Length: 348
Image (cartoon, one colour):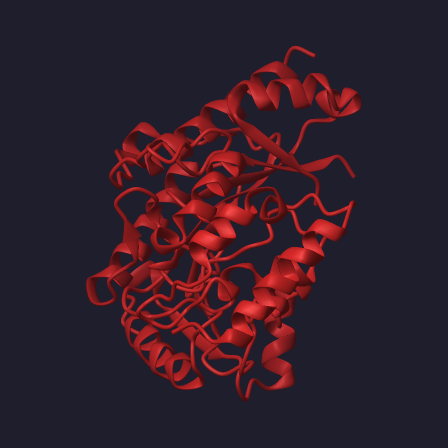
């Protein structure tokens, strides 16, 4: 069933990993002889093989993780590789652990993290979705890209009120439209070497597109890394408003387009780092006092399970956790973490 040439490529790629002393990917750590022999002869119903999982980490020895999901089934079919990788990356999510049911919870318990607008430049909540019944980017055909786009465009064009907007296909996009989207920080392009070597950017840009609302507070990407990337954002710290809008947008889409969700892993994504809630809730925030040290900060951020990115003293701070907690719990801890960071700058 699995081509001998494919088995040969798996064998050569395993050997490549072993011969590289600098390679420290999760792929190399967990694709043992035993796991490789257990998995190599399997194929999903949509036709994905272990190569469609691991090929990017063979090509990019400096990968962090080094593997992706070619479709929903792959997560369970290749569990002897995916399970240890997930456990490692999500910092304790064991093979027997189970993600909770979806729960966006009660938005009226959320607030503005900076009502006086002294610290937070902007607030963003992002999630990701795969559409049930389609392969992920490594195995989508050109036909499936086109058919999926038509379905997506249908549902996005039916947004009403605050979410009403325009869909912009990448195919045939004119230079002036492109410049406007760049100006709004809404454009995406063909993927980096990790995505290319994962077969995630084929038939570019067929079936790829960008949607945003008239107010430019809601943004969807179609067939960048996942089928859908859905983002709510605005100036200031009103996390309640941002998250409310996200829920409304995701919920609209779902009325016609069912999502891929696993009972154990939550929402399924091309990248294993994005499972569970798929949520990254972030702020762009200035904390000049704490910023000085950059350790007392790191130590406090980690204490509220936050992660500090950095794109003067403007930082991007977000929830670190994706799996093992609800959507509500992820957003609420980010909220509590930021309220505590602000409350301590006021004392520094």
